Image (cartoon, coloured by chain):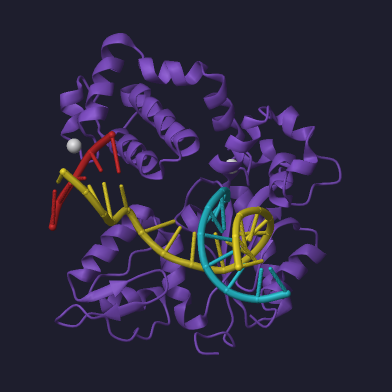
Chain colours: A purple, B yellow, C cyan, D red
Amino acid sequence: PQETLNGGITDMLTELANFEKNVSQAIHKYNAYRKAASVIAKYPHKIKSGAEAKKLPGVGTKIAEKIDEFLATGKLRKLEKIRQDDTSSSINFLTRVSGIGPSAARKFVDEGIKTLEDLRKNEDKLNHHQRIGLKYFGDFEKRIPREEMLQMQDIVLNEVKKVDSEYIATVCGSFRRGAESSGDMDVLLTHPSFTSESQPKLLHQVVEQLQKVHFITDTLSKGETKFMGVCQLPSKNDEKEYPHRRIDIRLIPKDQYYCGVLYFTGSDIFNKNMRAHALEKGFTINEYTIRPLGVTGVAGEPLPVDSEKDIFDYIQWKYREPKDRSE
DNA sequence: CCGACGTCGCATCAGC
DNA sequence: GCTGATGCG
DNA sequence: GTCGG
Ligand code: NA
Ligand code: NA
């Protein structure tokens, strides 16, 4: 619908969510508030009362009472109190640094480290990831327009093919689904020589090549199947430099690749629905495999999958393009 | 009432 | 040194 | 916090 409709409510809930996650360390309270904000963000009416909102799935008595207070007064007392409280605001703010989660942010604030300037003054208290998150603080909160994501895809597919024309690489996420912008880049990689019953630097070689051409600029973490790092499109010799961007690269067994591509293409709602329909047809899908279910509920051996459509055929569903996987 | 709520690879730390 | 827990994305 | 066994 429209922000003007329930943006005040959805903004209030998202702020309460962040405080649960970052200050309370109550991840489930956080996900509850976020779910409430999302169902409400999709409701195509300006909500008039908590009782109206409570009909919606994920809004309960508490959030109904909060909505009543917000509508009548324009604010939530408890959010106003958290907002001004120096400890809570600082903890919440510091978690915006990649690699600083609620635990580190609490420790920093417990010793007087509250601001980016405080972090910048205390480099030796930061691990390598947190230093990189600090270095690119502003860049990492920017969205990536699709035209840039295309240019980034072009570099990644070219360099991957240059290492070995046998690699398969798929940029997934909302971008795959036609998203006009993105938050990071999620690259899924496989090779025929890598199966579930068969890593030989096949991830390292792609990362190295991407580093050798100066696309990947920093490494947050890297092992034999998952890389998290920083990348940046090349400038134009005389043009504002592009911002640095977060990029993940996953190496997946070939026999699990299209289940991985399906899963990490999403959306989250679409995945829940396809998983649900799959159970009601006798199958279980996870990020790795589709397996048939016995009459007693015992999952059998994973079934051969060589394309996304294969999965749809198993469950007797017509192939849905990434565009049409919003839900 | 009261437990579930998504999963996991990797970096780092606790403990031995 | 090694194994397991915890934090984090 | 919300849901549901
Ligand atoms: Na409800
Ligand atoms: Na963070």
Q: Nearer the viewer, residue A236 or A70?
A: A70
Q: Nearer the viewer, residue A306 or A63?
A: A63
How many labels sit on residues? 0
Q: Nearer the viewer, residue A112 or A225?
A: A112
Whether residue A296 is visible here, answered yes or no, is yes
Residue A116 position, x and y percent, is: 70, 30
Residue A217 position, x and y percent, is: 77, 55
Q: Residue furthest right?
A: A237
Name the image quarter holding the N terminus of chain A: top left
Residue A173 position, x and y percent, is: 49, 57
Q: Quadrant of ligand 1?
A: top left
Whether residue A96 is visible here, answered yes or no, is no
User: Does residue A222 sit above or below A15 in this rendering?
Assistant: below
Q: Residue furthest top?
A: A73
Q: Residue at x 74, y 42 (%)?
A: A125
User: Does residue B15 sit above or below A103 in this rendering?
Assistant: below
Residue A314: name its quadrant. Answer: bottom left
Q: Residue at x 64, y 42 (%)?
A: A140
User: Does residue A19 sit above or below A134 in this rendering?
Assistant: above
Q: Residue at x 23, y 22 (%)?
A: A65
> On the rendered structure, is A80 left or right of A232?
left
Q: Residue at x 28, y 77 (%)?
A: A313
> On the rendered structure, is A77 left or right of A254?
left
